[PDB]
Image (tube, coloured by chain):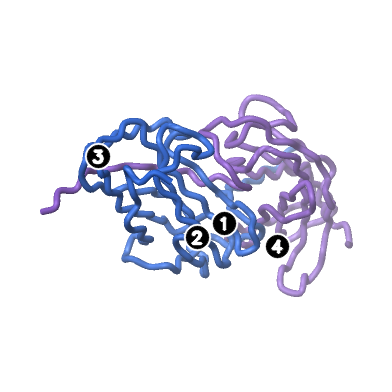
Chain colours: A purple, B blue
Amino acid sequence: MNFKAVIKEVRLKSEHGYTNNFPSGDTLFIELDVEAKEDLQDVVAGILIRDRFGQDIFGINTYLMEKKVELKKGKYLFTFKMPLNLAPGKYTLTVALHKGMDHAQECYHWIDNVCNFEVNGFKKEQFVGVCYLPTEFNYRKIPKL
Amino acid sequence: MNFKAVIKEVRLKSEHGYTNNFPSGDTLFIELDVEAKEDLQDVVAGILIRDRFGQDIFGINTYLMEKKVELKKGKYLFTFKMPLNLAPGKYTLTVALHKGMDHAQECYHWIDNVCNFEVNGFKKEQFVGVCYLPTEFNYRKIP
């Protein structure tokens, strides 16, 4: 990677305090301290949550999200917000900054498994399986009309 | 397994029609036709979506949802509604009735892989990994 922009610190945040231990469904904030050695006109930041055994659980880009990011030389705060709709367990976070995405016109900075965090308990209902889909349920008697 | 209540049909429906092929993030409607030969108190319905590789992706029941279900003899319609925040791929659905239980030890009806469905497109953004967590992103210049 060239290092025109750099991730200097990552912080995991609930809506009430910093922590690396969340109930399932709690809102997760990923904060990245970014520094841009120069002016970059198309920056793309990505996050990737992984399993305790290396399975990709979820990853996304600001390009995939259709969010344009232009930086000037200086320090920045990048924040990702998302419901932690994941089964209890042990996880790792991976992050990256680059310009392009197809054939990666260049890589600015990426940190493999920069962080460990865990998910314990349920803030919403209990469920089984890797992920949680918010669900509603109803039933009606139907007459043989 | 005791048949005092029986699941007689399962249907998958998008918000536009019955179908077994959904884009990722589309809303999924699971309809179960239930029949109650008699009066059942303390009924519990569950669904389980599974990988094409045996991985449990997501499962829940009406007990875990704290929704009490009491039937009188007759026909019923059970519906489950949920965003299919799942990676593109091929999946199976499993559904069951049991009385007021977990593990479904008093099971009225259990149908393994009652339905096959696939997720093919992306209705929301693209993502990688098993599931999709809806994400928001912001950036601010700081001193």
Asked whether disc 2 touches disc 1, contact meaning CB atoms under 8 Å apart, the reply is yes
How far apart marks 2 and 3 lie (CA) works out to: 27 Å
Please report, as a chain letter, where disc 3 is located: B
Q: Earlier in the sequence, mark 2 or mark 1?
A: 1
Q: Amino acid at mark 2?
A: Asn
How far apart marks 2 and 1 lie (CA) works out to: 8 Å
Residue with the most extreme left position: A145
Residue with the most extreme top position: A16
Q: Nearer the viewer, residue B109 or B86?
A: B109
Q: Earlier in the sequence, mark 2 or mark 3?
A: 3
Mark 3 and mark 1 on one chain: yes
Residue at the spot of label 2: B113
Q: Position of residue A80 (x, y in %)?
A: 65, 45
Residue at the spot of label 4: A42
Please report, as a chain letter, where disc 2 is located: B
- Numbered disc in front, either 3 or 4: 3
Is residue B143 in view from this perspective? no
The dot on residue A131 is: none
**A50 lies left or right of A135:** right
Mark 4 residue element: strand
Residue at the spot of label 3: B38
Please report, as a chain letter, where disc 1 is located: B
Q: State the residue at coordinates (41%, 56%).
A: B28
Residue at the spot of label 1: B50
Point out the image quarter for the C terminus of chain A: bottom left
